[PDB]
Image: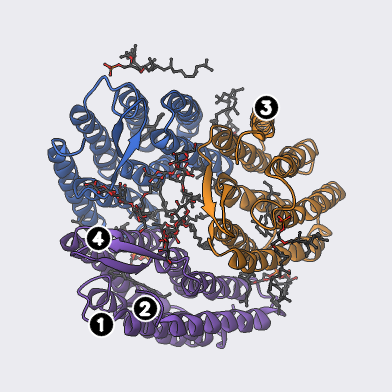
Chain colours: A orange, B purple, C blue
């Protein structure tokens, strides 16, 4: 159930909270409309994560789902968060590399399906079905990582060195971090309950804070965000 | 209830599924950013339809609603699908004709209301009220078909013949197909239960597959999508 | 509970309804793509408000939430409305002043959080927590009013007099009107139940109709919306 993981939820809330404040207090004197975009997108990512982490700490983002033959604790807030949060990160990568609107739409589309589908799976009552949805969700993610890695990099090679290198660091961080989510999910309370909800929430916390604050820090502290 | 229509749901899932694969495997070597947009938009339409048709086949997209004096089987997944799916189709028509942002916003707005309002109606408990919502939803749709037929055609007359003719075919297919939905709804399990849920699901399946795969095929196999 | 406020809900439905019709019947012969945008955005604001006010009058937009030690009547339809309705108004102000995409994204982002967070609060079961969410929601709003007042005005000073003056009127109307919502909420049935649901619904009605129809009238009847 949901009680012993309260500490990882409280620390996540705190970290996202400070992360938001920090980025806010850094983009204040930014005149460049391009840089402005990056700060806008990158700052909202942790702000949203903050509200959803708080809904979990306070119990609102937790629901109970019966499957297998039991009542399981499902933190649904994560999907609400990721629904808007993952496309924003992808938007950062797209602007940095100047991606075609066509591809930006395909990624956002793929990403919405990846999260929607993941939510469905998490709330499904027939234990066996949850893994069908997991399969579909992972197929979507692979498609997004494929484009970021092979498609975007190519696009980044045409920009100046500062942009290409920063994109390369962000690229490696998101590909590695994002792929940990489906595994954590599969082995956690949403799938085969091998790992306790306690450790699971700690894993997501490290992944979420790394994928947003870390990502943001790497991006917002470089000169790439400028023209 | 929901059991005998499983075959139309399974066939729809299959068809949307293959339809997605096919479009994916066709836009692969497309360099034109314009064409890229059309493939992106047109491919996501069936992909979304696939996930929602699967949620209905697996039972997740089905809920029970009391009205009249009974518990009625309401497939709510359809609205989730159409919410993002109908505006994307409209986006295809808009790009093909180069519509004003003002009008694109009015259509997407009208369309969101048409689906939201339709969802409300489907889930309302006071039998009589469901038809008030149906009335509002149909008013919205008529407004969208009006613009597509009279407004868009005019816009299409300024493009080269290939574009004008393809737009004309797509225009006639969507106007005819879309107007069948409110009728199916009115005479189906969501309204006056004249037609059984069995036949109803078969009707929607033919309409959905025609409105997306068919539409996509007509669009993606022409040279209109190019500059 | 929900019954004696039916009259304010019926009058709101009526007013939004007529307000929509009127704007529709005024933007008909508009050729200017810019003006077209304003009519599109401004017209959908009341159209959405109409569907949500109707869902409240008909009872669908009302739910029951236990907190304090009682079952409280929570009109959740308001959030559905405002979710899309407040960002559209902000879009009007942004176009009128020609705001940077960066800032438009920050405002829409801030605004989505303000409404989402407000919804959460309204539906939370732990009485004390509802005010934490109220605090976060108000912080977001203050951030939006800050930018509109200090940021946008500056942007408006570079436009021609007609635009600057209309923006100034709209600016003062929204800053004053918007700030009344959190107070009404805090002292209404969603917070410290000082004011009865009866008077509360009357307050929101005057605020909603003023913030949309009024706003729209001031905007759509000026020459500012033109190039
Ligand atoms: C403008 C855009 C384009 C914006 C669109 C936003 C919208 C569409 C997002 C939806 C996101 C999705 C992904 C999340 C939804 C998940 C969904 C499946 C889960 C739904 O449940 C939660 C929902 C409803 O809450 C509830 O109210 C009902 C009505 O009163 C009740 O009937 C429900 O029961 C109630 O559910 C709650 O309580 C349950 C309690 O049960 C009990 O448990 C306790 C335990 O101690 C005890 O045992 C009791 O006895 C027992 O009964 C609990 O189980 C439930 O889980 C739940 O707590 O909530 C609505 C959430 C709201 C939508 C989230 C807001 C998220 C943030 C703030 C969004 C910010 C977004 C901006 C827009 C992004 C901007 C950037 C872009 C530009 C890119
Ligand atoms: C980024 C964007 C801008 C994205 C925004 C996305 C979001 C806002 C979309 C919402 C779309 C709307 C239109 C659909 C919502 C409809 C809503 C009214 C219906 C809600 O119900 C379903 C919801 C919740 O599931 C449930 O979990 C709760 C919490 O644990 C429970 O409390 C609920 O009870 C539970 O409901 C399920 O189970 C019920 C079972 O009851 C039982 O029946 C069985 C029968 O055998 C038996 O009798 C049992 O005894 C009995 O108890 C059942 O009745 C319910 O129907 C339900 O199954 O589900 C959340 C769905 C999720 C939001 C859908 C995802 C859709 C897809 C993947 C979206 C892809 C979108 C991308 C974003 C588009 C990209 C393109 C654009 C760029 C244009
Ligand atoms: C394309 C976009 C990018 C679009 C995205 C749209 C989407 C994500 C918007 C979501 C907006 C959010 C903010 C609102 C959700 C609030 C949420 C917390 C509340 C959820 O509840 C309502 C929901 C479900 O209804 C229900 O169906 C379930 C399945 O069958 C049931 O299990 C639920 O119980 C049922 O709930 C209803 O009934 C309850 C009744 O209980 C009873 O009370 C009576 C009283 O007499 C009696 O006592 C009975 O005995 C007792 O049991 C009741 O309490 C509940 O409140 C409820 O009535 O509803 C879905 C709503 C739908 C999503 C709203 C549509 C809004 C409008 C039309 C949107 C227009 C938007 C366009 C897209 C904007 C365009 C412009 C942009 C370009 C900027
Ligand atoms: C514990 C916390 C995490 C909890 C907080 C609750 C939180 C959920 C609610 C807050 C809402 C929050 C999500 C909003 C985030 C917005 C974020 C995306 C900001 C990114 O923002 C980007 C910019 C857009 O820039 P601009 O206005 O267009 O500037 C134009 C300039 O004049 C140059 O013009 P030129 O090019 O022509 O030369 O933000 C605008 C720039 C402005 C000009 C400067 C803004 C200053 C700010 C008002 C002050 C910064 C914040 C404070 C340090 C403290 C924060 C308090 C919090 C409670 C709001
Ligand atoms: C080609 C495609 C198109 C077709 C494929 C897609 C689609 C069909 C779905 C494929 C997913 C499927 C193989 C799911 C596996 C989970 C399943 C075993 C659930 C069993 O659930 C019951 C558990 C109960 O264990 P208890 O809690 O300790 O008690 O049984 C005990 C369960 C065990 C504990 C589970 C061990 C699982 C892994 C071996 C753990 C090791 C981790 C992996 C090395 C890392 C990532 C996962 C990898 C499989 C991708
Ligand atoms: C049974 C199934 C229905 C179930 C599947 C589950 C499903 C729900 C999840 C999958 C996600 C899916 C929704 C995503 C759909 C995306 C779709 C919208 C694609 C439309 O996509 C449009 C393009 C965007 O193009 P680009 O990257 O910008 O190319 C630039 C080029 O270099 C030219 O540059 P120049 O102009 O300067 O000259 O997609 C990018 C083009 C790439 C360069 C090429 C992409 C190749 C693909 C990776 C391979 C195609 C797919 C495979 C045949 C099999 C599909 C497996 C499935 C499980 C993913
Ligand atoms: C009681 C009621 C509140 C309940 C109603 C239910 C309601 C919820 C459902 C209705 C949907 C509604 C929300 C839709 C609102 C849309 C709104 C945003 C409209 C704003 O709309 C802006 C424009 C977009 O313009 P354009 O088409 O691009 O014009 C191009 C022209 O050719 C110039 O070209 P040039 O620049 O190259 O020179 O709308 C398009 C302009 C068209 C060319 C003209 C349109 C005419 C209309 C069809 C008629 C107006 C409406 C009627 C008076 C009655 C309304 C009935 C109602 C039931 C629909
Ligand atoms: C610096 C920040 C970062 C930190 C702060 C943010 C966060 C911690 C939250 C701050 C909000 C907090 C102070 C909430 C106040 C409501 C609380 C008293 C609820 C009590 O709820 C119990 C009621 C029951 O009364 P019954 O219905 O008549 O029986 O007690 C009786 C209650 C009374 C009736 C309530 C009277 C309230 C006001 C005095 C009414 C006057 C209106 C104000 C002048 C106008 C706007 C409000 C102003 C406070 C902003
Ligand atoms: C806020 C930051 C990040 C990096 C979140 C990204 C999340 C995902 C890519 C989650 C993917 C899922 C998959 C691939 C399969 C099962 C369900 C998930 C939604 C967890
Ligand atoms: C996926 C393809 C299509 C063509 C779906 C379009 C759906 C509609 C236009 C549905 C309209 C409705 C109306 C007009 C009235 C009652 C409720 C509906 C939502 C079914
Ligand atoms: C349709 C018109 C308007 C002007 C609506 C605007 C609404 C708000 C700014 C509401 C703000 C809230 C705050 C600041 C705090 C508690 C919850 C609210 C969502 C009501």
Q: Mark 4 points at which residue?
A: C28
Q: What element carries label 1?
A: loop
Q: Are callouts 3 and 2 both on one chain? A: no
Element marked by disc 2: helix
At x 25%, y 82%, the residue is B195
Residue A207 location in percent, x, y? 74, 44
Checking the image for residue B153, the label placed there is 2
Disc 1, ligand 10: is the CB inside 8 Å? no
Q: Please name which of the two marks, 3 or 4, marks the residue nearer to the observer.
A: 3
Q: In this view, does C11 lie to the left or right of B214?
A: left
Above/below status of A6 relative to B100: above
Q: Residue B205, position in %: x, y?
A: 42, 82
Crowd tier of the residue under label 1, counting other residues whose Cα lies within 10 Å: few below 14, some 14–19, many 20 or above: some
Cβ atoms at labels 2 and 1 below 8 Å apart: no
**Cα–Cα gap, marks 1 and 3:** 58 Å
Cα separation between marks 2 and 1? 35 Å
Residues at discs 4 and 2 both on one chain: no
State ligand 9's quadrant. bottom right
In terms of secondary structure, where does tag 3 sit? helix
Q: In which quarter of the image is the N terminus of chain B?
A: bottom left
Which of disc 1 and disc 2 is earlier in sequence? 2
Q: Name the residue under label 3.
A: A18
Please state which of residues B163 and C74 is positioned toward the viewer in this rendering. C74
Secondary structure at badge 4 equals loop
Give the quadrant of residue B20.
Answer: bottom right
As measured in the structure, the alpha-carbon distance from the residue carrying label 4 to the one carrying label 2 is 17 Å
Task: Please name the residue that numbered disc 1 is placed on.
Answer: B195
Residue depicted at 51% across the width and 72% down the height: B58
Residue B224 showing in the rendered view: no
Residue C34, compared with residue A209, is above or below; it is: below
């Amino acid at each position: 159930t949901g009680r012993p993981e309260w500490i990882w939820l409280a620390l996540g809330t705190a970290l996202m909270g400070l992360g938001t404040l920090y980025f806010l207090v850094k983009g204040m004197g930014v005149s460049d409309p391009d840089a402005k975009k990056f700060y806008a997108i990158t700052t909202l990512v942790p702000a949203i994560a903050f509200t959803m982490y708080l809904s979990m700490l306070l119990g609102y983002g937790l629901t109970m789902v019966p499957f297998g033959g039991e009542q399981n604790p499902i933190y649904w807030a994560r999907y609400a968060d990721w629904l808007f949060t993952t496309p924003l990160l992808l938007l950062d990568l797209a602007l940095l590399v100047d991606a075609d609107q066509g591809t930006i739409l395909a990624l956002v589309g793929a990403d919405g399906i990846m999260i929607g589908t993941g939510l469905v799976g998490a709330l499904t009552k027939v234990y066996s079905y949850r893994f069908v949805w997991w399969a579909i969700s992972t197929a979507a993610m692979l498609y997004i990582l494929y484009v970021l890695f092979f498609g975007f990099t190519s696009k980044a090679e045409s920009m100046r060195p500062e942009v290409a290198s920063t994109f390369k660091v962000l690229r490696n961080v998101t590909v590695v971090l994002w792929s940990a989510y489906p595994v954590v999910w599969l082995i956690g309370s949403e799938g085969a309950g091998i790992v306790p909800l306690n450790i699971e929430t700690l894993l997501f916390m490290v992944l979420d804070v790394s994928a947003k604050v870390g990502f943001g820090l790497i991006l917002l502290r470089s000169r790439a965000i400028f023209g």
